[PDB]
Image 1: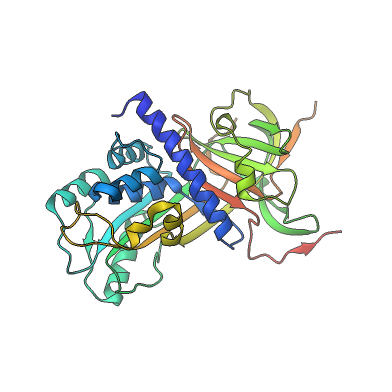
Image 2 (image 1 turned 180 degrees about the horizontal axis):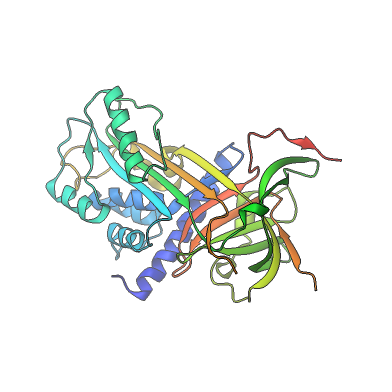
Length: 365
């Protein structure tokens, strides 16, 4: 159990890391939508931290904005383990090449904190790929299938990270009210989406005036929230929007809930990403050329690949059932945060520019 200041520091650190990673990926990537769990990446990097030493260890702390007096694996592991089950499925494993002996201390520690020991690769592209995917299928409990994709050899240390999110609203949506409706890609073009609907939903919703951004909080059951950040104009980027956000924008808005007509798209977002380039740019380039990971093996490791996948689903599922109201209509591009509400750690971030990439856009009148 960590201190009140210790979790306070972790929230601070994880927000800084989330911000850093999200921005970098946002400008690097070409995909229509974005979905990342910088937390999950942080947990994965804590695997490395557990076996890192000297400047490698230092750099891991520095990049994750973590105080070097605290223990990354313990903090992150403990935080995740205490989330309460059934909403986030997470898979984090270290895979190592055949000729690399692992320190017994590192196996036991990986076991204690991460639920499983790192695996040694057989040395055959065919057999290893199936074993990996099977284990990721098992650890996400069905949700994530066929993780990779491909595998070289040409492989020393592989760090795998897959995460699946599907939550339960504190207040459910009535699935009989969901309809195909217009989502505006821009001023002229629309796409059709399954629009969830509530006639009278309890909503904490407000405006950031000068930047022209609406913010709405949709509470999940287990001390989590889906926070919609929707600029009221089309031409924006992730970095400039983030720059306008504060802590109380994302965390514990004091504003009373208010009955609101709501339209919110169903979502099924999925991004897979090699983070070698991204993490190198953030300050971790030495991991991929000559790190000090003597905690794992006495000689002589290098991180070959950091493979991350986030899958997030939004649907009607939830626990509670129960003059004109105002309307909140999520039918413009937007940015989201999934927060944990007890302490303020961001679990997922993403950007939705098109909630139905397959659909043929329509030119509206």
